[PDB]
Amino acid sequence: GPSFPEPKVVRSQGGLLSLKLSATPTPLAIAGQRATLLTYGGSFPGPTLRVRPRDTVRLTLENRLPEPTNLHWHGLPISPKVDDPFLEIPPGESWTYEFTVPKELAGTFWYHPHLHGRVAPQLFAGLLGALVVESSLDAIPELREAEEHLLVLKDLALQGGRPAPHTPMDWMNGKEGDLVLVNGALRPTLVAQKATLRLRLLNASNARYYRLALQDHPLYLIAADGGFLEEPLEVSELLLAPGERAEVLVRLRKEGRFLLQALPYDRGAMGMMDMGGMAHAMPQGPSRPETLLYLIAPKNPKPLPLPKALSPFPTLPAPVVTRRLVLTEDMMAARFFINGQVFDHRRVDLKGQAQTVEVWEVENQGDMDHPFHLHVHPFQVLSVGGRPFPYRAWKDVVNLKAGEVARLLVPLREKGRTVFHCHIVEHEDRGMMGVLEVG
Ligand SMILES: [Cu+2]
Ligand SMILES: [Cu+2]
Ligand SMILES: [Cu+2]
Image 1 (cartoon, rainbow, N blue to C red):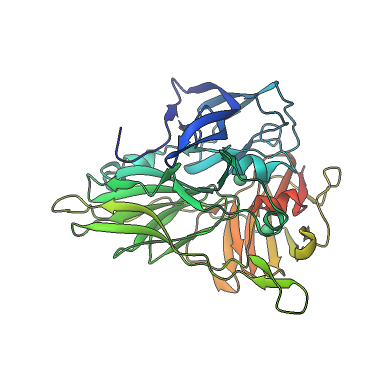
Image 2 (cartoon, rainbow, N blue to C red; image 1 turned 45 degrees about the horizontal axis):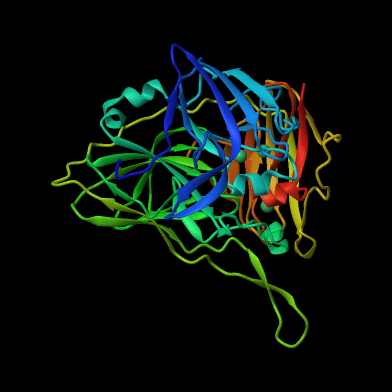
């Protein structure tokens, strides 16, 4: 097939994407070996859903797993009656998710399980897929003429032909795997046919971080989690935390082979160590460098000029409340807290008012990175760690290194009960989640 593996795409037809999608243990060939994963649509990753604003999505999820599950439409500002984090689809049962794609939306989003307590094993076993919202901006020549690819960054570990089980230490750190894959393939080769590439990036890992760098090239950031930037932003590297998305332009200036690497990154994962005195926790340190893919430039490459502008970011109304949400950890217990509390599905933690804007100060007082995710209501990151954020774009995950405070501008959109949580999904399963009610 094509030298570059990418998930199969399902496009909306006539303004409607209607599809039956089963969650099922699936035998398949993965990184040169046979394994049984948990998949949507018989594939890992699941199929990419490509839609346009104002399309209708009708996704009937059939649960063929031996455990209950549900779907989070990660990043979509839709009703929490649809993106329902509390719904349980029992084994053998089905549920139809139906929503309209918002008019003012563009970018790379994704779908995955969100049944509290089972998210980490279900997502690790392979239940995830992408959703792309096409934009009229994609028709400008600087984007139209680029060669576009989706890169689903997800790692895996196999044991006896199945996803490796979670250990106690996995529940503390978040589980990372030794197979560091792109679109389910082990270090694929991308033989570019155009000198400009448009790469949609998805970190769908449970916990692994990707400190992205392309040999000999900068990246041109054009979209964050949930929308375009106002203009391209040149970066030498790009950290993608669990759950985050980004889109970059790559401008191939010379012929040659270039590595896309996940450079060493210390996210504060811990191990255990015993030097006489009994065992005590010790930092794992930075991750080993990983090669993600091989990028081959075309002959005599003449890249397109970058777009001068993308999408103006909306001027938001003045905020009416400031929230403070403090993240803490009890590592040896693998318990994780927001303002000193663990998740309780019956407890409402924040009550806000639709169509107002709030300032959320999220403070990481732990020692690990925690990627903070808010459902339903995309936000503008104003600052992290006291540094002004270098661009304006909708995000829905923000990474917090130990000690850092992020200031977020949060317009409240759809009414109903939704959640916020760490997107190291083990931490969510172990209690680092709270409930927001919007009325
Ligand atoms: Cu998510
Ligand atoms: Cu969630
Ligand atoms: Cu966390």
